[PDB]
Length: 32
Length: 32
Length: 32
Length: 32
Ligand SMILES: [Cl-]
Ligand SMILES: [Cl-]
Ligand SMILES: [Cl-]
Ligand SMILES: [Cl-]
Ligand SMILES: [Cl-]
Ligand SMILES: [Cl-]
Ligand SMILES: [Cl-]
Ligand SMILES: [Cl-]
Ligand SMILES: [Cl-]
Ligand SMILES: [Cl-]
Ligand SMILES: [Cl-]
Ligand SMILES: [Cl-]
Ligand code: NA
Ligand code: NA
Image 1 (cartoon, rainbow over the protein chains, first blue to last red):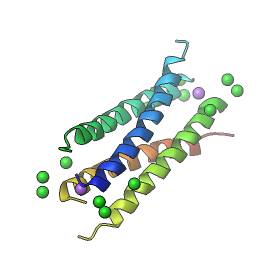
Image 2: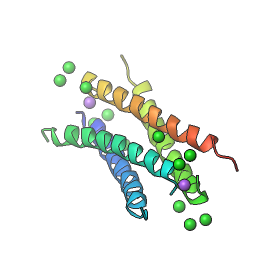
Image 3: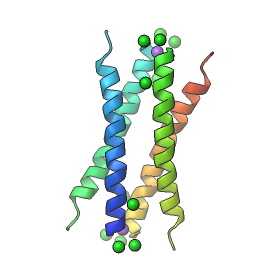
């Protein structure tokens, strides 16, 4: 990867991780 | 959450986890 | 959907749309 | 972008577009 692509992917990864974490918390919070 | 919403979010979560993992592997694979 | 689930999904959608747009712009910007 | 990065991002984009579309359909399907 180019530096620029690396940087971009790093920022994408951080955002996706945050979203995934929000979904995971919501699922975990469910009374079954 | 409704069952339907729970199910939907579960499947979304699984897909996002797979994508995040692909990005993480690509980043990790970079010679600095 | 519950109001809460609707609200959550709305915010998720907005974030994903922003990410997708960033990727699309990067791809479009490529000299082939 | 490298060819490899371009290819990767293309596939990521396709997957995200599919997910976003699923969320959008669910939201649109809601009786208010
Ligand atoms: Cl550079
Ligand atoms: Cl550059
Ligand atoms: Cl950047
Ligand atoms: Cl049901
Ligand atoms: Cl139902
Ligand atoms: Cl489903
Ligand atoms: Cl409420
Ligand atoms: Cl509530
Ligand atoms: Cl919220
Ligand atoms: Cl190559
Ligand atoms: Cl290569
Ligand atoms: Cl590939
Ligand atoms: Na719900
Ligand atoms: Na690159």
